[PDB]
Image (spheres, rainbow, N blue to C red):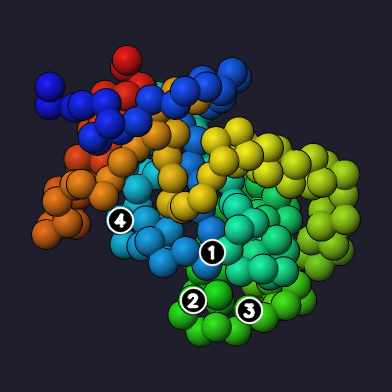
Amino acid sequence: AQYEDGKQYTTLEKPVAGAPQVLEFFSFFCPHCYQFEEVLHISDNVKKKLPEGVKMTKYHVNFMGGDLGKDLTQAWAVAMALGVEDKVTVPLFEGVQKTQTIRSASDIRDVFINAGIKGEEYDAAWNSFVVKSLVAQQEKAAADVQLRGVPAMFVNGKYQLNPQGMDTSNMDVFVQQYADTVKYLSEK
């Protein structure tokens, strides 16, 4: 076949009920994740190849970066709760990996302040039980697949994309193969 189980994707042994159509995991410490965001725009290119209105979800993980990694999962919960993912994603990647200015929870907060989230609103969200539940949801989704690596992409709670085999000589061809593979998996 052109797409083969065990090759371009893997079938999960335990389908995750109630999973969104597309579930991506990332870490702000993850070098490929930074590339997937700013240079490849993987999520937007996947979205464009899928039917309109399909549910796509993106969650942060704790397993990279120790204490700060877990602070970043809580900050990602804040970003989701406030709907400000598009305003903070690149500045968070830059602060962790490019300028290396994000060293503490206060430095994370500074990124949101600079992006225009009022401090009182950030602090209220950071301490909210809505955000605690979003933290729990991110941890539970990763635990459902014993996740050990990011970036990771899961389709319908049934298939994991495997990009390590795809050709990387041309960035746009890579993105097209990734998006077309997600579309194929979503149609299974």
Using a 10 Å C-alpha cutoff, classify the residue at mark 1 as few (fewer than 14 neighbours), some (14 to 19) or many (20 or more).
many
Residue at image location 32% in from the left, 15% down from the top: 188
Residue at image location 52% in from the left, 67% down from the top: 29
Q: Quadrant of the N terminus?
A: top left
Residue type for callout 4:
Leu
Image position of 176 (left or right of 169): right
Which secondary structure, mark 2? helix
Q: Which of 87 and 63 is in front in this view?
A: 63
Which secondary structure, mark 3? loop
Q: Name the residue under label 1.
A: 28
Image position of 20 (left or right of 180): right
Using a 10 Å C-alpha cutoff, classify the residue at mark 2 as few (fewer than 14 neighbours), some (14 to 19) or many (20 or more).
some
Q: Name the residue under label 4.
A: 40
- Considering only order in the chain, which callout, 1 or 4, is on the residue closer to the N terminus? 1
Vertical position of residue 37 compared to residue 83: above or below: below
Residue 80: percent from the left, percent from the top?
A: 66, 46
Q: Nearer the viewer, residue 139 or 127?
A: 139
Q: How far apart are marks 1 and 3 (CA)?
A: 11 Å
Q: Do the residues labelled 4 and 2 touch (CB within 8 Å)?
A: no
Q: Name the residue under label 2.
A: 97
Residue at image location 37% in from the left, 56% down from the top: 36
Residue type for callout 1:
Phe
